Length: 52
Length: 53
Length: 53
Image 1: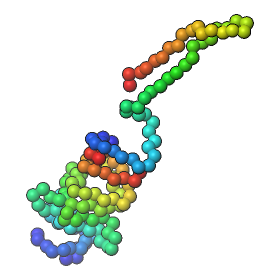
Image 2: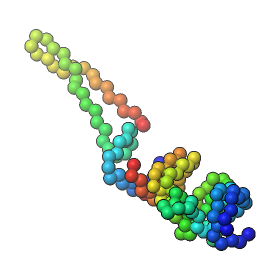
Image 3: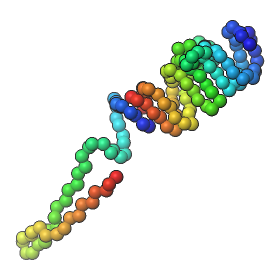
């Protein structure tokens, strides 16, 4: 379907992929290295964004 | 005029009916097409749409 | 052949026209249905669609 202007759904829209102006979000915590009773952040996190 | 199976080359009729009260399909002089289901193997190019689902 | 209203069992015509400069509705041997509005009480199953709204 190709809609050249407004499309108005008055019910529930069930879409698999949305390529609109919505936000994408990812999040992680750094790996923790510990000894005895104390730990500290030390490590790497890799975030990949596809150009789709 | 009542006719049986008739073959044709070109028809110019402004009102076509499938016959019956609640006609299954109908084409009126104003261009309205009334039907129960529409299966199209290509594109439906409309200026607007109103579908329930 | 010019006739008034006619009742039929089955028609086999490749070209059907509503009569007119820009016919309100038309059907051509290439499968095209041209109309101004289409009211369908059931489902429209099409391969592609192009609606403005």
